[PDB]
Amino acid sequence: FSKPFMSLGISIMIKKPQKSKPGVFSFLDPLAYEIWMCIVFAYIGVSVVLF
Amino acid sequence: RGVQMLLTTVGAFAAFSLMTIAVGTDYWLYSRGVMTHSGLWRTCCLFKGLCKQIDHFPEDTAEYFLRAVRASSIFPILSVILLFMGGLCIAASEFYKTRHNIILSAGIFFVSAGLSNIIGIIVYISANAYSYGWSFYFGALSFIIAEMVGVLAVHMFIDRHKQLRATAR
């Protein structure tokens, strides 16, 4: 054999994730998509109580 | 005069009908081990077509109290019975309104029944811990119509009170 011209090794291949950050759907992330409706319902109920 | 009263009456009738439809079926949707609908009494899968009462209350004491409240739907059934009583009171006060003070108590009981229905909706949402049913949205729409009907009822009551105060002077 001759001398090695191109050395190499063992690496790790992954799925390479991208910046998959959506828009409006990322806003209502941290609480829920259903607690807000109960919040609005209690809001209009307390306004009915005040009126 | 009577047009707003008829609008309040048909709004209470539509809210009672949507509350009846919310009691009936298709209140929620849950993917079991395929999706399956439920109406707070029994569950029906999408084998496919079989229906059974899946409201089994067993498998701190506050968890057992919350389970006892969520069992048998104690809040929304009594809320619907209170809405029926308020509708009967509004129907009795619509014809031959002798006393001008029963409408205020009927509206107060109607608003308290709406608040109890909202509390029962909060209990039914808290006991769920995937999609939702259409009768839950129908019950929410009946809650909105009941809030607007209570606003219109107390508006007609303060109009009648201002008319009585103007005629009494």
Image (spheres, rainbow, N blue to C red):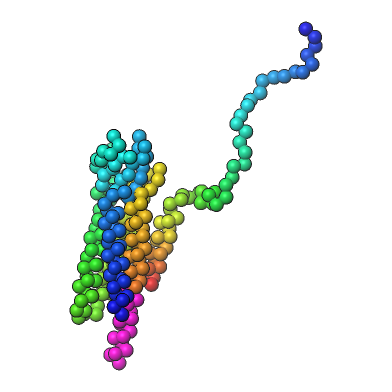
Residue B138 coordinates in the image, percent (x, y)? 34, 56
Q: How many marks?
A: 0
Residue B165 belongs to magenta span: yes
Return the residue found at the far top: A1
The foreground one among B164 and B31 is B31
Residue at x 24% of width, y 71% of height: B90
Residue B12: image quadrant is: bottom left
| Screen quadrant of the C terminus of chain B | bottom left
Residue B31 coordinates in the image, percent (x, y)? 37, 40
Residue A21 belongs to magenta span: no
Is the stretch drawn in magenta largely helix, strand or loop?
helix
The foreground one among B126 and B17 is B17
Residue B21: image quadrant is: bottom left
Please give left or right for residue A21 compared with residue B164 in the image.
right
Residue at x 38% of width, y 48% of height: B132
Please give left or right for residue B169 compared with residue B99 in the image.
right
Magenta residues, as a range? B153-169
Residue B48 coordinates in the image, percent (x, y)? 30, 37
Q: In this view, does A48 lie above or below B117?
A: below
Q: Is residue B124 above or below residue A50?
A: above
* Observer able to see residue B62: no
* Observer able to see residue B87: yes
Residue B144: image quadrant is: bottom left
Return the residue found at the far bottom: B169
